[PDB]
Every structure is written in C-alpha cells, then in structure tokens.
Amino acid sequence: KITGVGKETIGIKLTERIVTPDEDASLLDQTSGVPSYFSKGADRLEEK
Amino acid sequence: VYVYEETGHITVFAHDRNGNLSDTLKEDIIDALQDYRPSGIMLDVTGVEKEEVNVSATVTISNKSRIGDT
Amino acid sequence: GAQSFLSTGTTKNLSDDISNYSYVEVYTTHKTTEKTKGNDNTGTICHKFYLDGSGTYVCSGTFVSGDRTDTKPPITEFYRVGVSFKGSTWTLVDSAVQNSKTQYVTRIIGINMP
C-alpha cells in the first residue's frame, strides 16, 4: 500500500538468517553417512 | 555416571571423584570402554559443568508474629 | 596429557623445538602396586635431565607400597619409562612396569639455565 498522496518513496531491503546442519540435513557427515545427531560440518548465511 | 545417547555421537560424563573429573581418569576410562562401545559408533568422554543459580525469593506468612532470624 | 607406559613407539608434538632448551623436566604419575593407608596414588613426580642428546632419557625408580604389619613388610617395586626428543616431538621409547595398574607420562617442561 502506497498512500497515493505526496512523494511515495518506494525502496527495498534484505534480511539475514543462518542455516545449520539441520536447516539443511546435507551439512551432516560423509566419512561414513549423512542425517543424524553427532555428525556435523557446514552452515550458511541467507538474506531474504 | 550419566550417559547421553544420540544417533551421531555417544557422550559420557561423570562427577565421580569429589565432584570433579580428572584428565587421567578420562584417558583410563576411554581405553576401558572400547570393549563396551558399539562397532562403528563414535564414543566421546567429557567433563561435568555446573550452573550456579541466583534467586531472591519472597514469602508471605499468615502470622507475622512468628517471624525471626532462625 | 596422559600417555600410558605401555604405549611404546608413540610420538607426540611439543609446543616448541627441544633444541630451544638446555634442560627438560619429565613428569610421571603412578599408582603403586599396593594401597598405603588406602591410597595408591603417588602424586606427579619430576625427572630432570640435562639435554645431552641421548637417544633415550630414562626415568627409572622405585616405590615402597603397602602398610607394615609384623607379618608383612611393605613391598617394593621398580619402574622405567624411556623417552626421546626430536625437534618439535617426543616419543615414549620403552617401559617396564611390575603391577597390573597403568602408569603415565603426563608433563614435559622445557628449561633454560643460561
């Protein structure tokens, strides 16, 4: 909703997160095998 | 001794010796538990931590005449 | 740390090259054969060497353990651990133990007396 009155300044933003080994199960082990407790590697930033 | 179990890792921690665990006892017990651990499952041994709580409670007594230091 | 005397041939990293030291203290922690007054812990015992460049530094010694009665004098035991150094590493070369308990190398201190 723009108001439809005066200088309606339209403009953007973005929005941080973290992804764990649990937002993604894929950040769990491969010296043997993936989805479990006690088995952890990578994470991410993500920014909507 | 307390045991915490997870599909990934198995973690054992204890306050056996006067409320504290020593590194030497960890080394000794790691070697002993090799015969006991499951095949292909990781085993881990760690110490025990404590969290001191701070609390300032208030109590209302029906008979205020009873109150005292004791 | 805690390296068992039985773990002969094992090599561990030092925090600095041994050649930056003229002297070393090797610390050993033992359980005696018998309990004395209920306790078999010895404490942790210093062996001090000048670094002469020997292929083995030999912590060897003895404990008296067990309570004296009329019928039974305290027993005696012997122990050895041999250790060596190379650059930023040390090795447990050899050992001897006269009981079923585990004996440990536990600290290495570099010493300079310039």
Image (cartoon, rainbow, N blue to C red):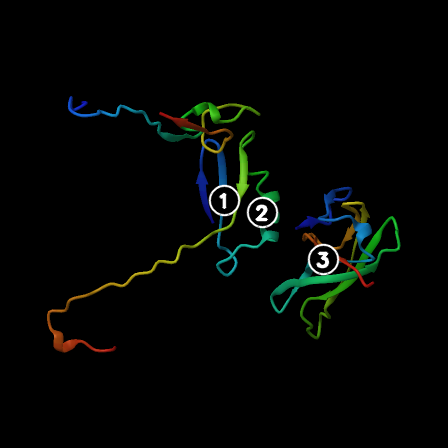
The image quarter in which residue C87 lies = top right
For residue C45, say whether it is visible.
Answer: yes
Q: Position of residue C94 (x, y in %)?
A: 80, 47
Disc 3 is placed on an element classified as strand
Q: Which residue is mark 2?
A: B29
In three-dimensional space, the C-alpha distance between marks 2 and 3, rounded to whole angstroms, equals 19 Å
Label 2 close to label 1 by CB (< 8 Å): yes
* A11 left or right of B27 in image: left
In three-dimensional space, the C-alpha distance between marks 2 and 1, rounded to whole angstroms, equals 10 Å
Residue at the image point whose x is 54% and y is 40% from the top: B44
Q: Number of callouts in the render?
A: 3
Which chain is indicated by disc 2?
B
Q: Which residue is mark 3?
A: C28
State the residue in front, C42 or A20: A20
Label 2 close to label 3 by CB (< 8 Å): no
Q: Position of residue B36 (x, y in %)?
A: 55, 38
Q: Which residue is mark 1?
A: B12
Residue at the image point whose x is 43% and y is 24% from the top: A25
For badge 1, the amino acid type reads: Val
For residue B37, say whether it is visible.
Answer: no
State the residue in front, C24 or B19: C24
Callout 1 crowding tier (Cα within 10 Å): few <14, some 14–19, many ≥20: some
* B33 left or right of C5 in image: left
Of the residues under marks 2 and 1, which one precedes in the sequence?
A: 1
Disc 2 is placed on an element classified as helix
Which chain is indicated by disc 1?
B
Q: Which mark is residue A31?
A: none
